[PDB]
Length: 51
Length: 123
Image 1 (spheres, rainbow over the protein chains, first blue to last red):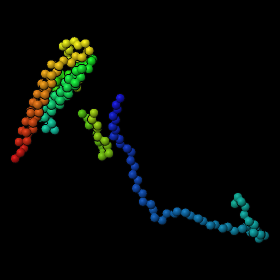
Image 2 (image 1 turned 90 degrees about the vertical axis):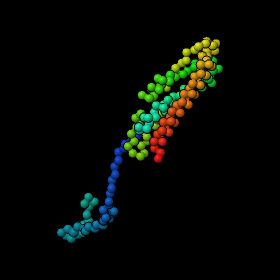
Image 3 (image 1 turned 90 degrees about the horizontal axis):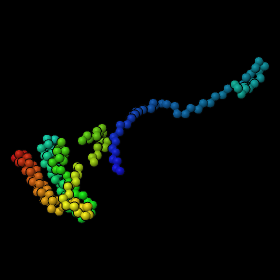
Image 4 (image 1 turned 120 degrees about the vertical axis):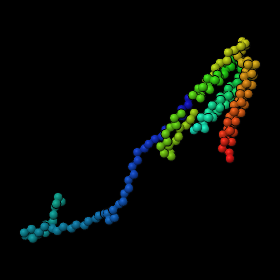
């Protein structure tokens, strides 16, 4: 037995050219502080877990 | 090419003479093999067949080009041997000498045609 096989293929091709924007954000860290709650009496009652 | 068409007939005749020469010499060499049949080719019919293909398409550079890759007639026996060998010395010796002569004649004709095509150009 003898099998000689030659195949020429055409392939899908996708070229993407990208120029990233200058000034993008890499990592953002934010510090927020809130106050207590002073009722009509004036006692600074702290907030709750849900809030 | 037109140059091939002019020299096609003599080249095919020369190649067929070489092939038949090989076949006749194989018949001579295997003369003593018991059960060997003497084979030969009909020169004229095979010359018609050769004188009377599709390279695969190459889209780019990497694509690989297409890769390329006669009928033997039994001789009618003359004398019946006991070991089944039908090779006759005299017949194939004459055929061998004739094929040698015709190969030389084909070489002469092809060389003359090439030499004429050359002296047309020389100047």
